Length: 221
Length: 341
Ligand SMILES: CCCCCCCCCCCCCCCCCC(=O)SCCNC(=O)CCNC(=O)[C@H](O)C(C)(C)COP(=O)(O)OP(=O)(O)OC[C@H]1O[C@@H](n2cnc3c(N)ncnc32)[C@H](O)[C@@H]1OP(=O)(O)O
Ligand SMILES: [Fe+2]
Ligand SMILES: [Fe+2]
Image 1: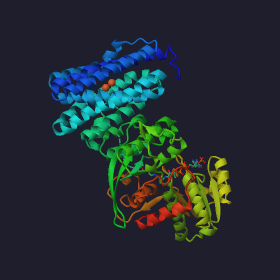
Image 2: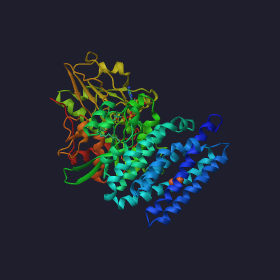
Image 3: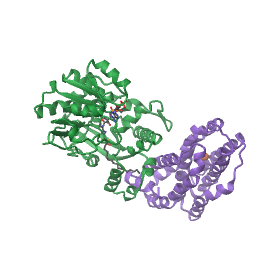
Image 4: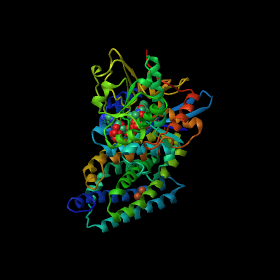
């Protein structure tokens, strides 16, 4: 690499740039819709939802940095299963499942993807992402503490919500596997950093180590 | 709070240990799963000293397997070492031992350069290789098996397989000054490092592994082999004493014949039962009492309060430190493993 030399790199960066900005976009509205569901923190959620909007602006600026055309059409079927499971769960008033999809599953996915990106990325893009990662780590802390205070009522639904959505993530990385290699990211390394971020969340929320192993493990991965 | 960071011998053992722990899903997996697995605290340890002090520890599974080195996954092997060290810091463990190959990888791949892991700066004063204590127990094991079998150590030939190593270099200085060994044979891969070890000691002949075995009364194995070799007893002298301190065993077969005495080297035995399940898998002769010496160093540092990187680097062990750590080892209830009979 060492050169965002095009015709290999620009083909692949097109999908990845579309995926990251959509996830930023999909995270942005996602965060606010909890404000209905959760009364007290409704102003905290808007702020955090804003952070996602500039994050998206900034990764759009990474589209300015290079002559790259994104495509949301491939990018939105990527989140289709993840989106629909959030859409349905919010309609039923299941706040506990809702926090898991966004605050834990999506942010750990962001954390992992940004940390692996930092070293390999184009010099200009490196600056912009190194700033974004410490926000995401706070994002995660929002769900961590809420579920911590509501552990005993939320535990049984948290287990259920993990079994259905965590497999999606295994599958999602495999679709992107060959693209991420083009940019100097290994598929294996991405999975490792998601598990570390995810297992750090679960442990603080209150799960014991034995539970954590079974739960992290879902998906044939 | 001391830490024990560790790994398994083989994918087969990972399969069995996974199912013994109850996770049937984990045992199904190939090398790829273990190459992306995160570190776990899988066991909590309480130990009582012979002085009566009580200390508490944790065991971290790194998820390294030596197969990864043969399969040229140096990228992966390094992550596993750094995630495990990072993991033990996040949990506020005051001193941790880098068991097995984790200490090897740390030196061999200049991981002191990469101390920023996930943005958390690794405080090297929170880790030890455990190698100082391992070198002592091996020297005490050679002395002890010499008397058990009626051998006069001071007129005997001892080969050190891995003599330029961290442990191997230390064993050679102790076998030189503290026990006055007859002859010293030096075996290794690199030649420059062997030449300076002969210059430091002022003694010892350098031979390959093929030529050193038939001329050795004592064979001390302390080499970083991923696999482990097949030795035929006809190549060896009678009697022959093999001390195999490697992980995995540098002896890929149980070498048995008339005059062949095999001791599992680098092991110590505590005087009180220990609350744990981990040494059960490690094939310890008595798993509630016995353990590896480098794990015992972490307990020793914790009993004494020497929160520091007591063993570090390579070729830095001195006799003064081996003596210190050995004093503390005896005083707290630990004894070298002896010949089985
Ligand atoms: C979702 C998650 C799923 C989780 C599920 C899993 C849950 C289950 C986990 C529960 C597990 C419970 C079991 C716990 C495991 C217990 C075991 C402990 O972990 S670990 C056990 C604790 N650890 C132990 O066992 C400690 C004992 N072991 C040791 O002390 C060390 O490993 C050592 C002695 C072997 C290394 O020595 P050291 O000095 O440190 O190494 P150096 O590099 O300095 O030395 C290198 C020199 O060696 C020479 N050399 C190399 N190759 C050759 C050759 N072919 N010919 C000749 N010579 C050779 C060579 O010359 C070289 O220099 P050069 O000439 O090459 O330059
Ligand atoms: Fe974001
Ligand atoms: Fe976010």
